[PDB]
Amino acid sequence: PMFIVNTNVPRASVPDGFLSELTQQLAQATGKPPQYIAVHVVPDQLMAFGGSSEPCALCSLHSIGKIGGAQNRSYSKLLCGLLAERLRISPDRVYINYYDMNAANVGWNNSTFA
Amino acid sequence: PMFIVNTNVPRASVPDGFLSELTQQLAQATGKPPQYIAVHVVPDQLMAFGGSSEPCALCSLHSIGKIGGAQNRSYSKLLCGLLAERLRISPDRVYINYYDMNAANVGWNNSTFA
Amino acid sequence: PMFIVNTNVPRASVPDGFLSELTQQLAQATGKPPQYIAVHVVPDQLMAFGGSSEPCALCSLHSIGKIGGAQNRSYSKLLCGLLAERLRISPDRVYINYYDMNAANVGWNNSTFA
Ligand SMILES: *C(=S)NCc1cccnc1
Ligand SMILES: *C(=S)NCc1cccnc1
Ligand SMILES: *C(=S)NCc1cccnc1
């Protein structure tokens, strides 16, 4: 699993523990060891959401499996909660695109997971 | 709909009003209300297109529906036209990836759109 | 084909010529002309892999075809090798997401491909 957040929140507003918190929470949510989880936060972005430049986030969650209708609804609550508390983003200004990756289409360690 | 532009054009070259213009032009193109539209512009990027560092862009349009053969041609004309007029990027140094997202795979406000 | 690498290594760690090399090597690997190859390198990112901040990368390769089981293994070996030799990123701290794009879903030069 790989989680990416793109936001107009300033860099100084991103807590130093946020990547570790996300790692850990996503391990619990997906049932995967934290070692497998990658997280990426991109602050200071030129963005608008609904025509407004109030705090917002455009995010992606990729996983080989563990993606689906009910799971994604659950992830949205987890992730909106974390973004709300730690980045002070309203949950209605967050989009999360979910990608169920085929193992043959994820490279790692000189090969793929297939 | 969510539109992202990644470009090597410098930040000072992005006009005031660009994000608003994109929002408005996308609302017209897609028929979706501007409240649901997100736009994200990322200048000053280390990029090459065709081995050259002349102005270029790599973009993405995600939408739940409103993606398809003729629609995407229309969008490419619109969006390359904006990049050319506003950012002075040649249309032949732009790629736009189009993604027709399943509503179950788009999270927003503590749920998905399914 | 379009290749994007996001990394926590610093910009000064990216060697002169890296985007050229990537262009060249990807042309060789995909068989596509270099003119159509786009590369994008994003250093100095706020990242974690497995909860560690040691050098890592999150990458994407998009191509209209030339994506598949064996191909992707080959590309992973290539690209992990480059990131290791050039950017001193361990291969086991790189993920590469591969995307086989439908030509109708790729915009370029005011239109889309087929
Ligand atoms: C998230 S995409 N993790 C990739 C992965 C999956 C299974 C085992 N190891 C890494
Ligand atoms: C762009 S991805 N807008 C989101 C959306 C689209 C259609 C219906 N509801 C939300
Ligand atoms: C990479 S996505 N290159 C795009 C492309 C592919 C084939 C022919 N022309 C452009």
Image: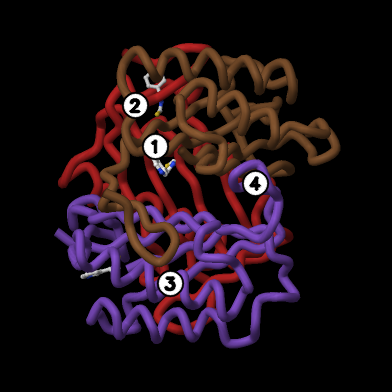
Chain colours: A red, B purple, C brown
The reply to whether label 3 and label 2 mark residues of one chain is no
Q: Are marks 1 and 3 in contact (CB under 8 Å)?
A: no
Measured Cα–Cα span from mark 4 to mark 1: 16 Å
Q: Residue at x 46, y 55 (%)?
A: B95
Residue B24 is marked as: none
Say which residue label 4 marks.
Answer: B48
Measured Cα–Cα span from mark 3 to mark 2: 27 Å
Amino acid found under the numbered disc labelled 3: Leu
Task: Assign ligand 1 to one image quadrant.
Answer: top left
Residue A27 place in picture, x, y as percent = 41, 30
Residue A94 place in picture, x, y as percent = 40, 64
Measured Cα–Cα span from mark 2 to mark 4: 22 Å
Q: Residue at x 59, y 37 (%)?
A: C5
Q: Name the N-terminal-most of marks 3 and 4.
A: 4
Measured Cα–Cα span from mark 1 to mark 3: 21 Å
Residue C108 horizontal side relative to residue A109, left or right: left
The reply to whether label 1 and label 3 mark residues of one chain is no
Say which residue label 3 marks.
Answer: B79
